[PDB]
Amino acid sequence: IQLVQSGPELKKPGETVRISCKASDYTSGMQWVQQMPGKGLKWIGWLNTQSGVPEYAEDFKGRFAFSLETTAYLQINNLKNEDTATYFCATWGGNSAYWGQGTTLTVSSAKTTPPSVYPLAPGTNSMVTLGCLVKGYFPEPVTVTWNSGSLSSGVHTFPAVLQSDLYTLSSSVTVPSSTWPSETVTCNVAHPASSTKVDKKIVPR
Amino acid sequence: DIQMTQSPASLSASVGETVTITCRASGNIHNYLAWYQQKQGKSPQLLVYNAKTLADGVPSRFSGSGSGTQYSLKINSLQPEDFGTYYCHHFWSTPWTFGGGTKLEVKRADAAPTVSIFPPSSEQLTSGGASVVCFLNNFYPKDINVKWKIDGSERQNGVLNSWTDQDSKDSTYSMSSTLTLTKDEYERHNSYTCEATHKTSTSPIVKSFNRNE
Image (cartoon, each protein chain N blue to C red):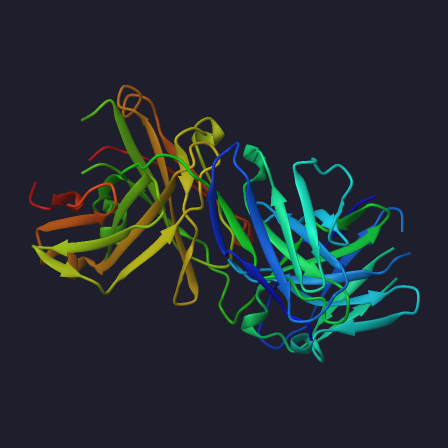
């Protein structure tokens, strides 16, 4: 048994969004859970598929509603910035629980903007740390790789911080001084929302 | 409305040790409690339901106990995949509330951060901007503070920080500090210093650069 949810969503304050959760086998009933970035799990309510009776939690009564079809829906009305989060669906049966992969929802008035990628090079040891600054983009996320994925060791991308209505983030990569600048080191930034892809070669100063 | 109070919020242990996580209900829930595990924002995995029954496929080092309003999840002989966040969730009466959660992190030896400072790039300066970046990589424990200095004077405005989660491969934490300025503000000064304060040193762990060099 598996639960699949609809892809990411981007809406403006005050709009409506419908999130689907379709099972493969379809009994029991289902529930929805909300999880804001960096926060704990919050219960939205559950739906007794048998009696069709939905039951919501105080903070979700009014703007959140459950519906069926093998596809349960979670529709939210009059979206607020604070509705930004990941929403999970879940059912139960036998000796376990089944949850959806989750669905991200971003609710902002912000305008979809591609990122500006800058090379972060050293102002020498056997190891050298390089980086890439991904500034002023919206919305999330933004996938960052190094040398098309060839460089996956000594690499880590920091979480994005929100400034203005735009996100900024940077990626760090550590390689041998014997490798760079001799061998090419390029960071690859992809921003799905803008269908953008940028490559920045890390050139020594 | 029965609320769940979960403690501790944070826990540090090492592979092989045993930890206990507790949840207390503001009212009797008659064992209608479920324990979940969540890793890297991914989907939660049921560990125990009805307070003491293990879900399908859950290792036996996991066990739940309790009754009435007091319950706890015990994990013994911690395996490396056991580290993540845990949550209790009752379903006795609506609303089925979750506990505040418990972040279980890996305990390893102390490690001072490796500091790197990066001047604004040519491309950015050309556009009129000047973001000075500093990396404080691979340190442990996670507590750390960063302080910027321009021509020997502390700088607080224009600074934005980001913190990674415990790395899955070396159990360390990393941080990113960025001082944003305009091409003009940036060119009015010569020395830029990134200073970290970590328990692995009673002195600042620094790295800096000078435009005029």
